[PDB]
Length: 49
DNA sequence: TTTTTTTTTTTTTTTTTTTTTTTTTTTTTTTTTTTTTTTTTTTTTTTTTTTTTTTTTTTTTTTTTTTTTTTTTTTTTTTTTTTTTTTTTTTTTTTTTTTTTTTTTTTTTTTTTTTTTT
View 1: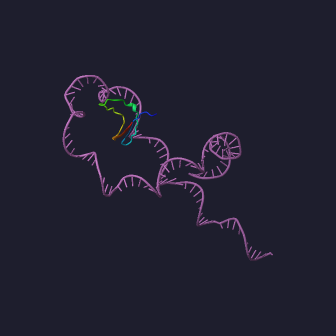
View 2: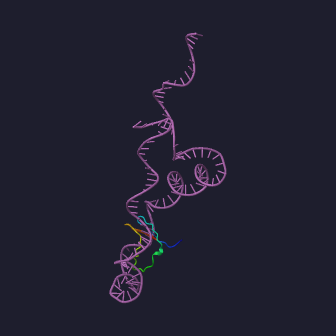
Protein backbone atom coordinates (compact mmCIF):
# COMPACT_ATOMS: atom_id res chain seq x y z
CA UNK A 1 0.00 0.00 0.00
CA UNK A 2 1.21 3.68 0.52
CA UNK A 3 2.25 3.83 4.24
CA UNK A 4 4.88 6.28 5.50
CA UNK A 5 8.22 4.45 5.23
CA UNK A 6 11.80 5.45 6.06
CA UNK A 7 14.73 4.86 3.71
CA UNK A 8 18.43 5.55 4.13
CA UNK A 9 21.60 5.03 2.10
CA UNK A 10 25.10 5.05 3.61
CA UNK A 11 28.65 4.98 2.31
CA UNK A 12 29.22 1.58 0.72
CA UNK A 13 26.34 -0.92 0.61
CA UNK A 14 23.13 0.24 2.34
CA UNK A 15 19.61 0.71 0.93
CA UNK A 16 17.80 -0.35 4.11
CA UNK A 17 14.10 0.57 4.46
CA UNK A 18 12.24 0.24 7.80
CA UNK A 19 8.62 1.10 8.48
CA UNK A 20 7.89 4.43 10.11
CA UNK A 21 5.65 3.22 12.95
CA UNK A 22 8.41 1.38 14.84
CA UNK A 23 9.82 4.69 16.19
CA UNK A 24 7.71 6.64 18.70
CA UNK A 25 7.51 10.29 19.73
CA UNK A 26 10.06 11.78 22.12
CA UNK A 27 10.65 15.12 23.81
CA UNK A 28 13.45 17.30 22.48
CA UNK A 29 16.16 16.93 25.09
CA UNK A 30 16.75 13.16 25.40
CA UNK A 31 17.04 11.54 21.95
CA UNK A 32 19.51 8.64 21.57
CA UNK A 33 16.97 6.04 20.45
CA UNK A 34 19.76 3.73 19.21
CA UNK A 35 18.35 2.44 15.95
CA UNK A 36 19.69 -0.92 14.81
CA UNK A 37 21.42 -0.25 11.48
CA UNK A 38 24.72 -2.13 11.37
CA UNK A 39 27.60 -0.22 9.77
CA UNK A 40 31.24 -1.35 9.59
CA UNK A 41 33.48 1.74 9.54
CA UNK A 42 31.35 3.73 7.07
CA UNK A 43 29.34 6.96 7.38
CA UNK A 44 25.63 7.55 6.86
CA UNK A 45 24.66 9.98 4.09
CA UNK A 46 20.89 10.12 3.49
CA UNK A 47 17.52 9.65 5.16
CA UNK A 48 14.14 10.01 3.42
CA UNK A 49 10.56 9.86 4.68
C1' DT B 1 49.17 -77.39 -87.71
C1' DT B 2 51.98 -73.70 -86.03
C1' DT B 3 52.39 -69.10 -85.00
C1' DT B 4 50.92 -63.91 -84.05
C1' DT B 5 47.95 -59.68 -81.88
C1' DT B 6 45.23 -57.87 -78.15
C1' DT B 7 42.54 -57.77 -73.58
C1' DT B 8 42.18 -57.68 -68.54
C1' DT B 9 43.17 -58.86 -63.26
C1' DT B 10 46.62 -59.89 -60.81
C1' DT B 11 52.36 -59.89 -58.56
C1' DT B 12 50.47 -55.71 -56.59
C1' DT B 13 53.30 -51.34 -53.09
C1' DT B 14 53.04 -46.21 -52.61
C1' DT B 15 50.28 -41.56 -52.39
C1' DT B 16 46.17 -39.38 -50.83
C1' DT B 17 42.38 -39.16 -47.93
C1' DT B 18 39.56 -40.61 -44.18
C1' DT B 19 38.63 -42.44 -39.68
C1' DT B 20 39.70 -43.09 -34.77
C1' DT B 21 42.44 -42.32 -30.37
C1' DT B 22 43.95 -38.14 -27.86
C1' DT B 23 44.34 -34.27 -23.99
C1' DT B 24 44.37 -27.24 -23.13
C1' DT B 25 40.98 -23.94 -22.03
C1' DT B 26 36.45 -21.49 -20.04
C1' DT B 27 32.20 -23.00 -17.79
C1' DT B 28 30.03 -26.02 -13.71
C1' DT B 29 29.75 -27.67 -9.14
C1' DT B 30 30.63 -28.95 -3.75
C1' DT B 31 33.02 -27.02 0.13
C1' DT B 32 34.10 -23.52 3.84
C1' DT B 33 33.57 -18.96 5.22
C1' DT B 34 31.25 -14.83 6.18
C1' DT B 35 26.39 -11.81 6.32
C1' DT B 36 21.38 -12.10 8.36
C1' DT B 37 17.29 -13.11 12.02
C1' DT B 38 14.98 -14.67 16.64
C1' DT B 39 14.89 -15.55 21.81
C1' DT B 40 16.81 -14.64 27.67
C1' DT B 41 17.90 -11.68 30.81
C1' DT B 42 20.62 -8.56 32.24
C1' DT B 43 22.70 -4.83 34.48
C1' DT B 44 21.97 -1.27 32.31
C1' DT B 45 19.83 2.39 29.82
C1' DT B 46 16.31 5.44 29.39
C1' DT B 47 11.12 8.05 29.97
C1' DT B 48 8.70 11.19 33.01
C1' DT B 49 7.33 14.88 37.61
C1' DT B 50 9.36 18.84 40.83
C1' DT B 51 13.11 22.58 42.13
C1' DT B 52 16.62 25.55 40.84
C1' DT B 53 20.22 29.43 39.30
C1' DT B 54 21.35 30.54 34.85
C1' DT B 55 22.67 33.16 30.11
C1' DT B 56 20.79 34.72 25.78
C1' DT B 57 16.95 37.87 23.59
C1' DT B 58 14.78 41.83 23.40
C1' DT B 59 13.89 48.24 25.13
C1' DT B 60 17.56 51.74 22.40
C1' DT B 61 21.55 53.66 19.37
C1' DT B 62 26.08 53.21 16.25
C1' DT B 63 28.63 52.32 11.82
C1' DT B 64 30.92 49.80 7.58
C1' DT B 65 31.53 46.33 4.37
C1' DT B 66 28.66 43.66 2.17
C1' DT B 67 24.64 45.41 -0.75
C1' DT B 68 23.88 48.91 -4.29
C1' DT B 69 25.37 49.67 -9.25
C1' DT B 70 26.72 49.87 -15.12
C1' DT B 71 29.13 47.93 -18.44
C1' DT B 72 33.06 44.84 -21.59
C1' DT B 73 33.84 40.78 -23.20
C1' DT B 74 34.39 36.74 -22.47
C1' DT B 75 32.33 31.33 -22.95
C1' DT B 76 29.07 28.55 -21.59
C1' DT B 77 24.94 27.69 -24.03
C1' DT B 78 22.36 26.35 -28.00
C1' DT B 79 21.90 24.62 -32.80
C1' DT B 80 22.91 21.19 -36.56
C1' DT B 81 24.77 16.98 -37.78
C1' DT B 82 26.18 12.30 -37.19
C1' DT B 83 27.33 7.92 -34.43
C1' DT B 84 26.05 4.41 -30.56
C1' DT B 85 23.16 2.46 -27.82
C1' DT B 86 18.50 1.10 -26.33
C1' DT B 87 14.10 -0.75 -27.27
C1' DT B 88 10.23 -2.82 -29.81
C1' DT B 89 7.63 -5.08 -34.64
C1' DT B 90 8.71 -8.87 -37.39
C1' DT B 91 10.28 -13.32 -38.55
C1' DT B 92 11.86 -17.92 -37.69
C1' DT B 93 12.13 -22.15 -35.15
C1' DT B 94 10.66 -25.59 -31.77
C1' DT B 95 7.29 -28.08 -28.58
C1' DT B 96 2.79 -30.15 -27.18
C1' DT B 97 -1.74 -31.99 -28.15
C1' DT B 98 -4.21 -37.22 -30.52
C1' DT B 99 -4.62 -41.01 -34.11
C1' DT B 100 -1.50 -43.08 -37.77
C1' DT B 101 3.24 -45.18 -40.40
C1' DT B 102 7.63 -47.44 -39.09
C1' DT B 103 11.17 -49.60 -36.11
C1' DT B 104 15.38 -50.62 -31.89
C1' DT B 105 17.48 -52.82 -27.35
C1' DT B 106 19.47 -55.19 -22.00
C1' DT B 107 19.50 -59.50 -19.18
C1' DT B 108 18.63 -65.44 -17.26
C1' DT B 109 19.19 -70.51 -18.13
C1' DT B 110 22.60 -74.96 -20.57
C1' DT B 111 25.64 -76.87 -23.82
C1' DT B 112 28.75 -76.73 -27.64
C1' DT B 113 31.84 -74.41 -30.61
C1' DT B 114 35.44 -70.68 -32.00
C1' DT B 115 39.13 -67.40 -30.58
C1' DT B 116 42.59 -65.39 -27.65
C1' DT B 117 46.31 -65.74 -23.82
C1' DT B 118 49.64 -68.68 -20.65
